[PDB]
Image 1 (cartoon, rainbow, N blue to C red):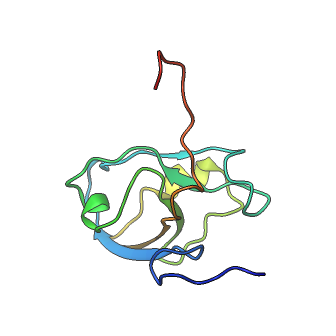
Image 2: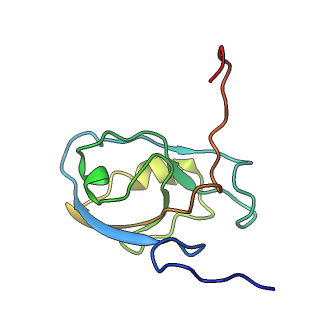
Length: 119
């Protein structure tokens, strides 16, 4: 009774890469490095988007949101390293860069309910 395949875009292997142009300026999103969120993976941590502004490339891709997990960047693994290398590598170099990301199905990354009246 293993896992079954449904779609080629929405599955446990949810993965997508897109090349975007970045110039000397500020990004439209802010990434963050957290822990104890998705232990289903390996014994470490990954980088996930923390904010996005619709209309920007990171949103022009087609199906992007606040949570996309960045895997690589033009063939430059970041795993093992600490947020330090994450913010540094974020700088990049050339404009045209290939960024690897992953968009898992709804139910894997449940947002936490911060103090409030109801919501």
